[PDB]
Image: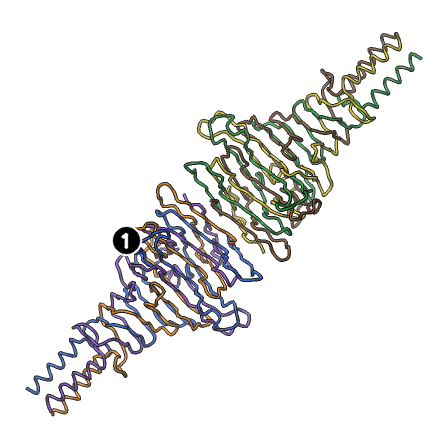
Chain colours: A brown, B green, C yellow, D orange, E blue, F purple
Amino acid sequence: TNAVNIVMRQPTTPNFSSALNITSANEGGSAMQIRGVEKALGTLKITHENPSVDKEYDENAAALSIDIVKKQKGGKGTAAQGIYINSTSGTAGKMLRIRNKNKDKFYVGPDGDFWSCASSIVDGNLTVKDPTSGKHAATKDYVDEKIAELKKLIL
Amino acid sequence: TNAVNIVMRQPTTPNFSSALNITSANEGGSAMQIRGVEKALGTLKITHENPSVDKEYDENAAALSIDIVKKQKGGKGTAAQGIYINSTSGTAGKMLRIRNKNKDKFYVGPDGDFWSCASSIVDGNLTVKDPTSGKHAATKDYVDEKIAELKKLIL
Amino acid sequence: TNAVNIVMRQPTTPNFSSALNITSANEGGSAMQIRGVEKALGTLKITHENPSVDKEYDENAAALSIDIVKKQKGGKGTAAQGIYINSTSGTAGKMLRIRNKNKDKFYVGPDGDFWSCASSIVDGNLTVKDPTSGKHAATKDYVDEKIAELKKLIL
Amino acid sequence: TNAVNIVMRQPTTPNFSSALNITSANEGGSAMQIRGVEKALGTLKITHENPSVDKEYDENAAALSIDIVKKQKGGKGTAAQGIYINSTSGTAGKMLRIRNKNKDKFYVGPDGDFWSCASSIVDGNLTVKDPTSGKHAATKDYVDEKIAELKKLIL
Amino acid sequence: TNAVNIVMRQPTTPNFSSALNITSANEGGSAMQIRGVEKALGTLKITHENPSVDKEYDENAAALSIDIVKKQKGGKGTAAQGIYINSTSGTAGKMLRIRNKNKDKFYVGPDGDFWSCASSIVDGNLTVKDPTSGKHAATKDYVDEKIAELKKLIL
Amino acid sequence: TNAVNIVMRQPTTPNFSSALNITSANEGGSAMQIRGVEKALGTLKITHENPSVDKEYDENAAALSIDIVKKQKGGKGTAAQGIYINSTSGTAGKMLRIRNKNKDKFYVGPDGDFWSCASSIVDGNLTVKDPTSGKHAATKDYVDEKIAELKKLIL
């Protein structure tokens, strides 16, 4: 079926080895590039399967893990980005869509709007526009204004 | 140009086959690893191209698709993560940057702050800090306080 | 150690070439697929290293770069998604976890709740539920109600 | 089973393309190297299968085809060898063993002796040592001597 | 060092699996092609190493094993060749050179002459030209002639 | 065109590195296997090109180089073969065909007969059958017999 298949079989003892390991020392080009024309699949599909029946066994595991590091010998830092997503021609699809058991839980749409299915938290302020609707969040401004308006009506 | 090029040509009829398919049964190491030193590109770059001129044809497609599953025969669950992004040494760049037609739409910065370019939605509450600025969102606390303060001034 | 290792050595002059370049013209299947059973690692791990000691040198670089494009000759658009994350069986782990120097900065949990470590911004409204707690953000509704309630008490 | 499998499926029309194509421009190292420790198989095994039921269809085909050429732009020639076989430590096995339907037809042994199962031909002379046995081939010398010996006995 | 390295580690029990397995179903092109520009090495180098200290353990093994077979389902035969060696531009080097412990044992030169280091055998006749030198092998013709010449001198 | 292409570009200084390097430590299976269905090409085609215009520059080079070695740490020897060629079903084609500038110089046919285009040499005897034809080589037997026959006719 597949043009190239790379299989790492189960070793007797787990070890740190990979089926496929790629390294480039060329700062002028992507170490790896993929291009596909899928009608309804991912150009890259990554599946992580719990190696154990135990449902908490793989709690530190991930399908995709990214690290962003300084130059190994003597680097002063890095300003590289983690994930960069673009559509040079423009897309109508969701830029980031997160589902759990095939139900949408969080997404970022093509206009940069987000939708979250549950109560969330910002350890800081959220800057927003003034509400123009019932369930829009109220700014300090809107509160202060309805206050000052009611102070007046008591003279 | 490239060290290794893998090409799957257009079949007469589309089928489920991949240019490159990797599977590891070793729970001790990443099935695949990539490392690059790009000055201005992605270490991995994934491009998805609509296979059709029709702009809605690829609405279920994605550049990157991730699935997180239990052990196939008899697993009780999984606690594996979807995408994990870190910078062990620390980065000044945006951890997640989403653009559409080369304009920023949503990002998560290195301090975990987010910026969204459009009206968004949480089906639940948002916990925030008290506003200290005009367009900061107001907490139940801030509202209740300006209320209690105005009750007093009417004795 | 690794089953397959692909190395692109440092060229004398940087150029656009990749260690590994994959292209599929088959719209019926993922150009590439990866599956692993890691106990505590990423099924795919991508590391980007600053090629320079200079901490701002790689400011346009990324570990993962995604582009979503129309059909090259004559496409009218695309509705393809950037990143799609699912757990067909269901996971307890965070769907998106972003850390900087091994400290959590932003995440999206399995229920679609998000947590951000810093003040954030929406250029638009945020729709939320009515606050039921001190530091929950207040809706236009909650503000208007405590206003109308205080108007009444002044008759 | 295999660590890496590369499959080129049957195209609708045959064309000149290969499953795997390797080119090196480095004159200092082998474009490819293979090493194995087989107990009873070839380190490399090549099978050619007639693509047709017709028994004469593949008469120009070969399992292994070697070409030895001059430098493409302006070379004056080459002195490169076709096949070089050595045993740096020394082997007791046949250096070249040729069988047809699992019966030996021709071989070259570890001392450089050959054995051929059928009448053969040299378009030229064969230089040999004087016969010391019935079915050894006779040199001009041996013939001339038995002649001169018989001339004498007729005085 | 190498651009691509494929390693199959020692399994606990030997099995029939390969580091690299290639199959083409395209009758129009070589399943695999290699091209190099070595100054003093093989374009392909194959090393077989005895897996055992025992000097007779690998007596059925080979560095290169070739099989030439009919079409699997219903073929009537094949006329494919085993090894085909050419030099389209012409070479001064030996076409086949066989050494054991770095000493020449057998070769075929660029003119098709062979040299064998030991007594050899043809189960059949050898056709040769008439001897013109002492140690050239004698034809039936040369023998018969020196006979008829000596019959005459006895009248 | 090709499913997998591996290219090692010209380095500034030649070094010992390969485009593709394969090693198996599994004594139970071929380190590599190739299978093709070519109508008129080699299942594997190896081309060596002189890296220099100088026609003697590559005099130690080869298209295919084979080494047969003992186990590295403490082996007592090896009985492995260099090249093993078979046709399990049987072939009508030449088992080994050697050409120089597209003219046949030496071959071994499917019955194990050889043909050489030039004067050749065996440092030893050649055992052959008695001549039954003019240009067949004469055995010690045939010579001795025509001698004894002529002794008789002189009584």
Q: Does the rendering let one see residue B11?
A: yes
- Residue D145 is situated, as x and y percent measured from the top left of the image, at 19, 85
- Residue F24 is situated, as x and y percent measured from the top left of the image, at 51, 60
| Residue nearer the viewer, B133 or E46 | E46
| Residue nearer the viewer, E78 or D129 | E78
Judge from the rendering whether residue D99 lies leftward or rightward of residue A115; answer left or right: left
| Label 1: element kind | loop
Task: Using the image, determine if residue F106 lies above or below residue B92.
Answer: below
Task: Using the image, determine if residue A134 lies above or below residue C105.
Answer: above
Three-letter code, disc 1:
Glu
Total residue callouts: 1
Question: Which residue is under mark 1?
Answer: D56
- Residue B31 is situated, as x and y percent measured from the top left of the image, at 59, 48
Judge from the rendering whether residue F137 lies leftward or rightward of residue A112; answer left or right: left
Please name the residue shown 23% across and 79% down the image. Answer: F139
The answer to which image quadrant residue A91 occupies is top right
Q: Does the rendering let one see residue C52?
A: no
Task: Using the image, determine if residue A23 lies above or below residue C120.
Answer: below
